[PDB]
Length: 53
Picture (cartoon, rainbow, N blue to C red):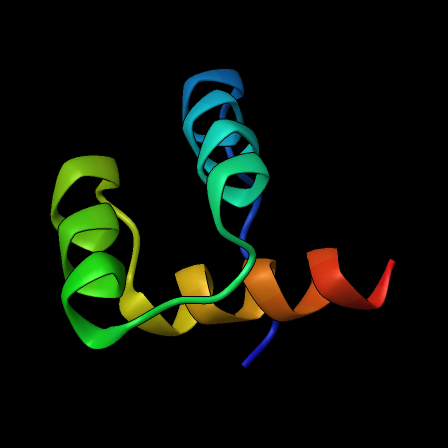
């Protein structure tokens, strides 16, 4: 799955979340998806990519 483009707001949330905990659980992935309007797949990819970088 190719990565979508994230808005500034979505990125703001993801960065703060990543800085609290770099690893996702199911419930946290679901909360992010529902609060960000992003597919869970996109959330997982962003976290993986962020750890990679």
